[PDB]
Image: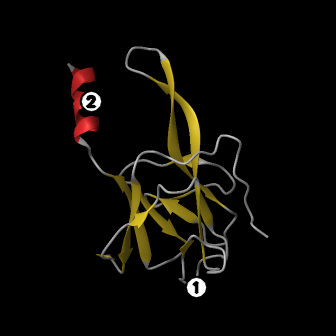
Amino acid sequence: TLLFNEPPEARKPSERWRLYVFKDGEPLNEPLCLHRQSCYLFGRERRIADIPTDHPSCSKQHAVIQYREMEKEKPDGMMGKQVKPYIMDLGSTNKTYINESPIEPQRYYELFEKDTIKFGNSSREYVLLHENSAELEHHHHHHHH
């Protein structure tokens, strides 16, 4: 009955990704946690959606944000890995939009900080972010200097 599978490379992220919500262009009180499981299902069906998308233009199971472990090139050219967010539309009639442009269904699209996401013709929109850290900032300063 779920319309998606998680791939072999699925992993819970360590980065504290959160999803800020807008209702008619104004913010809710708190962002949604987007970093405590490896996949988040968006859809109108409250029985199975992780994040319900109640607008009537939205499909029962509309889109997933899937965390995937991929390669990461370090500044020094040596190899590591990272876990990053990807969105996939599940063949919704009314589409999934990243930064105002629709995506091809059944294909993973990498997501980035500050991306805006909209499902169908919903009056709601979402912005993806994560926090800054002293550790993160020091690490970046080290590599820059």
Q: Nearer the viewer, residue 58 or 39?
A: 39
Nearer the observer: mark 1 or 2; the answer is 2
Q: Which numbered disc, 1 or 2, marks the residue that appears first in the sequence? A: 1
Q: Answer with the quarter of the image where residue 31 lies.
A: bottom left
Residue 111 in picture, x, y percent from top left: 48, 49
Residue type at mark 1 is Pro
Q: In the rendered view, does 100 fall on the left or right side of 53?
A: left
Residue 140: assigned label: 2
Residue at image coords 60%, 77%: 58
Q: Which residue, given by chain and number where applicable, does mark 1 sit on?
A: 56
In the image, farthest residue toward the right: 1
Q: Position of residue 47 (x, y in %)?
A: 66, 80
Q: Pointer 1 and pointer 2: residues touching (CB < 8 Å)?
A: no
121 left or right of 45 in image = left
Question: What x and y, as percent, mark residue 59?
Answer: 65, 76
Q: Give the residue at x 27% y 46%.
A: 132
Residue at x 26% of width, y 29% of height: 140
Q: Amino acid at mark 2?
A: His
Q: Residues within 10 Å of mark 2 (few under 14, many from 20)?
A: few
Numbered disc 2: secondary structure = helix
Q: Where in the figure is residue 80, as x and y percent of width and height?
A: 50, 24
Quarter occupied by the C terminus: top left
Relative horizontal placement of residue 57, taking residue 138 as reference (left or right): right
Mark 1 to mark 2 CA distance (whole Å): 44 Å
- Asked if 42 appears above or below 141 in the picture, the reply is below
The residue lying at 23 percent from left, 36 percent from top is 137
Label ID, residue 66: none
Q: Up-down: is 91 above or below 131?
A: below
Circle 1: element type: loop
